[PDB]
Length: 187
Length: 187
Image (tube, rainbow over all chains, first blue to last red; front, side, top):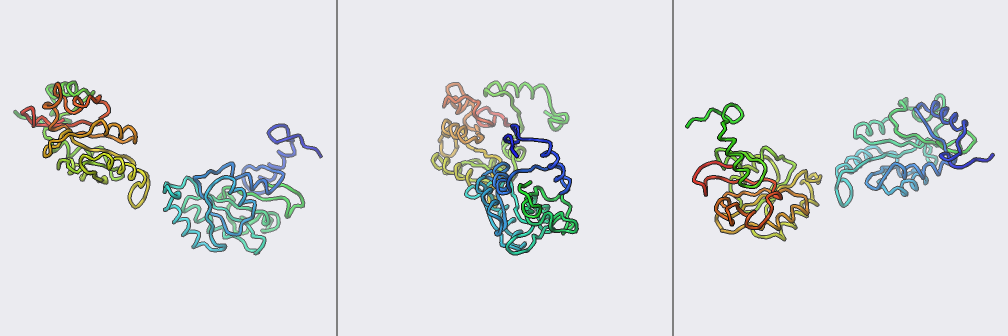
């Protein structure tokens, strides 16, 4: 029941490797990592791959962990009304045109954050149209499948199975084992 | 008394090579070209090395040939009042900040055009301060020594000799043999 330390120092075992391989095969992607907390995952991801010259366009109903993780990095934030895609496209166009505030230089990067299922409304996210705009405007996509994985779809793979979307158009997928697997952690 | 054709086709002789070498040695630069007209030189230079995403900051008293050459290329033009350097620095700063019009992207290039001696006022150009700002703000310098070369300076080299400026801070120097050499052409 005792760990050794960080994964980089001594903490890794073969069980971690097996779990990562099995999760990656289950989702349909190439590789995966596992952590000991979902809140920590969402809080420490964006700090790692973002900066203060980038932009994040996230839904207004996102979880608190995503907000904390984005706040820790330094990027700019703009939100669109929940379940509205014309507003999303309009915001994307306007923010590409305007550029960085007070300097008007081109945005170095644009990331879109959403959720597979919002667990206060019960609604889904319009994944096919999100893929359409991300391909058209060269954005990136981040999806949080905390409540979708394991419990939705014909065989339980989430919203990609529900909408028939190939799980290669989504740049980063993350979820937790807490909701529908009776365990703890994230990936 | 007959030429053959363009310099690229058959028109070159050894006399052209000797003249280019001697002019380059006389001015103090590394290499030079000679043409058959000064108006044509000024009209066809900027078309060759400029574009529509660049900016030209020229004095308000420049010759007509410079204006035609700049107009033929497509670049944007802004002028500063004659004999005023605070306005020049202010314009440089504002135009670097603002960027390309209606798009606000960074200026791809900035070129400053002046004259060694303005042959309607009799005044010179403040070469040392022009060099100071071009070095400070990373601009480029173009000088038109039509009336200065041959007839000004301790030994007749122009405004570089008058101000003691090393003729390496000036990116492009051009003049004519019409005024003070009793001939025709330009370099």
